[PDB]
Image (cartoon, coloured by chain):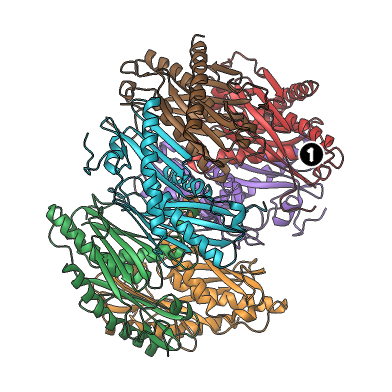
Chain colours: A cyan, B brown, C red, D green, E purple, F orange
Amino acid sequence: MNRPSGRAADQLRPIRITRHYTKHAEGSVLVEFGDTKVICTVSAESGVPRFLKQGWLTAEYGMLPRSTGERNQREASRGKQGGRTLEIQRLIGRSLRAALDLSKLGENTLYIDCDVIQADGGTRTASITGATVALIDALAVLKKRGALKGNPLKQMVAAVSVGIYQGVPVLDLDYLEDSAAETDLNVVMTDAGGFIEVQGTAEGAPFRPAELNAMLELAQQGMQELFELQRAALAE
Amino acid sequence: MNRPSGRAADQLRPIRITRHYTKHAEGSVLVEFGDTKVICTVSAESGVPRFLKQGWLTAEYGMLPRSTGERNQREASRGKQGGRTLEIQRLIGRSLRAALDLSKLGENTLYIDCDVIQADGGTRTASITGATVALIDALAVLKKRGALKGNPLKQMVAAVSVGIYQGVPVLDLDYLEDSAAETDLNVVMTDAGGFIEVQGTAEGAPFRPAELNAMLELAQQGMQELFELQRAALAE
Amino acid sequence: MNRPSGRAADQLRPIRITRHYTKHAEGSVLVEFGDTKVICTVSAESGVPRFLKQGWLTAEYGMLPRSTGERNQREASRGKQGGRTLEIQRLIGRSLRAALDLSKLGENTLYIDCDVIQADGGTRTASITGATVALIDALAVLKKRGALKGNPLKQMVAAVSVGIYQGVPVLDLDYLEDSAAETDLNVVMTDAGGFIEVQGTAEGAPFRPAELNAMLELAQQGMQELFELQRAALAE
Amino acid sequence: MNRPSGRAADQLRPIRITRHYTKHAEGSVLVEFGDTKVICTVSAESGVPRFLKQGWLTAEYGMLPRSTGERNQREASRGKQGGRTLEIQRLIGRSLRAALDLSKLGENTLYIDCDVIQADGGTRTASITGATVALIDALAVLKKRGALKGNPLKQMVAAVSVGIYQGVPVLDLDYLEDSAAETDLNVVMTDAGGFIEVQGTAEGAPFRPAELNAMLELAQQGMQELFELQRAALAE
Amino acid sequence: MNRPSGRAADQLRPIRITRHYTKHAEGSVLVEFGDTKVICTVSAESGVPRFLKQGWLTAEYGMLPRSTGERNQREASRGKQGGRTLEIQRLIGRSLRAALDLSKLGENTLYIDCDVIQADGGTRTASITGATVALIDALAVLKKRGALKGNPLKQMVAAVSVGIYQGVPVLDLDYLEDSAAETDLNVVMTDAGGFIEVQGTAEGAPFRPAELNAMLELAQQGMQELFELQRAALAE
Amino acid sequence: MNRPSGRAADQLRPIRITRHYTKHAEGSVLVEFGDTKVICTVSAESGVPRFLKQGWLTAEYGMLPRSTGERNQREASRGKQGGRTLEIQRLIGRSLRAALDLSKLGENTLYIDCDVIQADGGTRTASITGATVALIDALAVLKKRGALKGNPLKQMVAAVSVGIYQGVPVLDLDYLEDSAAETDLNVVMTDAGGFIEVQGTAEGAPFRPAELNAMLELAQQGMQELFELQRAALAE
């Protein structure tokens, strides 16, 4: 009935995307979903893992220890990456690989690094959306370097979450809502309107078909504003 | 058009569930989805992690090195659990926690161990379905021991996968189909017909809404046969 | 004076060996020493470690968390293999390497995986005895593939334990006796009647020469029944 | 003779300090030494390690994978912190502990997290200088919370490097100079003008006493501008 | 027929035992079996692990990287202890625990550290023999401190190896012989003449009963000279 | 005013250097700074890391668990090297690399291993000083083997500490003084009189310029006696 941020159940948080955020990566973006801020960089490396087939792209995720309300243990010192981290990491990699025609990438490898400097819900969705813009900038770099084999960009990709808060589907969850909601959904989509990733979990009352479809439709709606924001950013 | 096992697109593999499979655990089940065979045990431990609120249940997943066509590196010797393992593990724990009213469990902790002795697709879905039966047997043990605080069983839980093979939604994927399919879906549901977990990924052509709903409906259909098989098993 | 299982001090537990237990490995056996049940697989891999000399065989050991009376911590999640595991592992590898003329194996590597699904004493001895049968089946596979350089099978190998229970040497210890006994002995032998491995430890009263020789003679006696069981199994 | 940035041998890079940079920590600062940008947060935690004596402060250091010209392996995934990291970490902790009268801190623990978002030389020196400002802000937070036992701030602390470039002592090294110089020096000082930390290494020609003293004097000179910048920042 | 060191098949290497070797431990011994030199220390710590029953003793083993002909990787930097190390470690602990009546030890814990400064065969046997002397010295320390509950020394313990070199049982193997021999035996015994540990492995021709007994008798013979050397050392 | 050992504020502890200490390494030295005793070995290995440029030298540091007053946890079993260890290790490597003209070393790699058998302050300084002598012996070995490309020895290198004890600069700190002193300094120098390494830390009152220079001058003075001791040792 009333979202903490006073936002409308179908309203995205204020979103900002800053390209060329840090100077070393071939692509670097500061993406902001409200108070969730993540630095997304793409590093172009010559060669490929165990292939011979097309190029490759892999991704990692990290969080600064006090990017969260309560300090979270630095994984570097704990000597291990938790399940959440790997989960988010794998999601990012799949999502961005889906936006590419790896064959046209050449025998190069792209390293996507998404690091959360401030968390407030939806870091994975902000990561995906922001990393895609960094990816485009990177491909332009490799193109100018004549390291590509055509334009490997199959299509743009954005992501967003939805959750049942106070019994109502709400779009783009902040930290408070995410903690409260027992049913949520993270979705990754393309321009065409296809789903590349759909993940929904119910901790309390299991969500029924109608709910899922409603959450899916809400996600699809906000998704369009994201593709818009990305194009805007890419237009300088 | 033609499933390798000659199975019908809406037909489950032959399924078997053997209770009291190994003698130490309070609940032990050998669950078989065709050639996928997994040993699911539940270990009842007194006490709880960092609580004071209700009981607790946590789960782990493992695979014998040659449970797979090509030997997979033993995690114990690699000194680390891969992303797949943690992913499957977390899924199992959430799924089985959703079947319980933790408050009625008492201040006890349940350890779910799902180990694959032979893999051929759907180990996570077989795990969930089989572990639930082991769970019931375990609760009976604790009940007789007067360690419970009521009947913590909220509802049965089963799981199953679906994938687009040769362009058609097929139910309960074996290894061949899983490798071939670029779009799949794993689903966890309750008796009532609610969804507790829905995960779909598209590697190639992104799946559109209609596809998803069709896969979801197929999953829901086979799901009923599973709840049936579990009740049968539990009836000795 | 009275063995818990009411077995005679010179009587082996009921033993069963099932070949082709799981379908992927070139050799797979379910070996059962009473309630001790272990899955032993042999995986044939092309190539060799750091050699140029003959083939190679190496072995690993694992236990399902509730294969034991009290749940034992999964090594994969503990991120380390305990001393017991490595000890048993090394023993298995040496034992099975001793049964082979590595030169005739070719430039192939055999991976022996012994995983305990249910423990009740003597898992290492059951492992050795069962893995040998899996080994034979595997060599037949490689032979048909024309990957061998003759018949690398030098001789069969079996293993068994003995322990001083209630002051009397008893053959093939179950869990209860093993815990009670302060003096035990694990032995690995060949058809010819030679010793390839003899390990005895005394926690309480140190065992004197006569005791050792008596335990050794008991071990040697039961050993013959094992070689018999293996040949039977191999005869379909 | 000519510094890459065209800076004068005794001129600091443009320096900026932004307080309240991220919203969760009791103290958060974005410190910038030219292109070197580091996020420094201080997290106030109740209690103390193994004490009974005074409070405590400990520090960690991290670098985003593409904060450097060439992507540096994420320590979280490498499962270990390199020597450089620990070295810098220990330095930070000592430096900031020296600025405090731990007894007046109370039985609280301060966690200093310095994460490099963009590196270009002097990250450790920027870290120290920036973290001190975050520290002040944090102490104000704890004061208002009535968790202190007086004002634990003994004195401000800043740091800076010096190196022999093209045969001349230069102040505050950027990445290029640092790589070129074979002799450098990192120094940590207080307002009073005391040294809390002096570290100099010579890879090529060993530096003689006169050189050291000259580098020390240069460091001391720029140091004053830093204390000035910190006070300015703290004045809103 | 001819031992490299020209030693007689039943002759021990020159043995030396130096007590109070290093000044911190309650017991410290430099034990030398020919060119094999090991520093054995015993550290007395108040309290016990997970007990309430008696005291405790545990042991560790280490080797300097160039204590061996070819540099062996430092385990500290490899981040793991190999199988050999754990094996030897466990052996040492069992052996020295067998020499004690833990109940009379008090609620104290003894840490045995055996570090090889120079290896040339038989480090484990030299370790055991030397650590026992360090143990005695330590117990005297605790006695004077009135931390004991009687005299926990049940009996002295020494160890030695035997191996088939050039077809002949030889006592106390140096590095050359150990590498050459395919059949060896490590034995741990007490004053009374009992066996606490017997381990024999055959890499080539399996050793028959007569061989084993012959090796055992040789081991038992040299063993007496060791108990003699220990008493001598303990007599200042 | 009064050093525990009754030593004069400008007097080194009794120092001894024994070459050819252990028989396997190309260079092996037992270096003793009073009660601080460290075994320093140099291992000559053919080849080089990731080079093509000159040779290479790298170093490791270790401490026996009871080389210290209170037993320190063995890093091998803790599965990690602490900050102190890496710090000391890096220092050693830099120091000894500075004594060499790597180009003349050939395409060989030198492994320096410094292991403390007994600690009482200044292990790092004793390590450096002793390892240099082991280094010389090693180069002679490689020379005779005709594996060098000239004489890679640029100059001798020694190290020593200084600390403010009871308000007075004292040379070569033992354990007691090191613990007491809040301001100390470790220095590494060459024959010529150059500084290759200068590290000073102040825990309490920050040290002022005059203090530093005084500590530096004291260090430089004792340094000369060390170069003398090394030459003496090298003269048989």
The answer to whether A111 appears left or right of B65 in the picture is left
Say if B82 sits above or below E7 in the image.
above
Say if A111 sits above or below C93 in the image.
below
Chain of the residue under the numbered disc 1 shown in the image: C
What residue appears at the point 68 percent right and 25 percent down from the top-left corner? C21
Q: Can residue C167 be seen in this view?
A: no
The answer to whether C235 appears left or right of B159 in the picture is right
Q: Please give the residue where the numbered disc 1 appears in the rendered image.
A: C100
User: How far across and how far down the image is residue A87, in percent?
Assistant: 45, 43
Q: Residues within 10 Å of mark 1 (few under 14, many from 20)?
A: many
User: How far across and how far down the image is residue A75, in percent?
Assistant: 41, 51
User: How far across and how far down the image is residue B83, in percent?
Assistant: 51, 42
Q: Can residue A198 be seen in this view?
A: yes
The answer to whether D235 appears left or right of A185 in the picture is left
Q: In which quarter of the image is residue F170?
A: bottom left
What residue appears at the point 59 percent right and 52 percent down from the top-left corner? A102
Q: Which residue lies furthest to the right in this view?
A: C150
Say what amino acid the circle numbered 1 marks: Leu
Say if C15 sits above or below C136 in the image.
above
**Element on which disc 1 rests:** loop
Between D159 and B183, the residue placed more toward the observer is B183
What residue appears at the point 39 percent right and 30 percent down from the top-left corner? A212
Q: In which quarter of the image is residue F109?
A: bottom right
